[PDB]
Image (tube, rainbow, N blue to C red; front, side):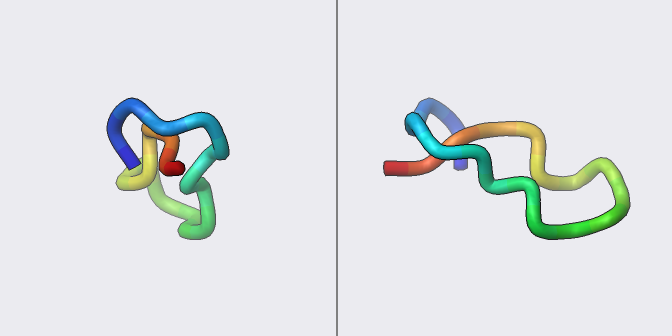
Length: 21
């Protein structure tokens, strides 16, 4: 996400570098 709690790391690359909620 951006400032969430759970990691939005679902992709392999380095796109998802935040957390969602």
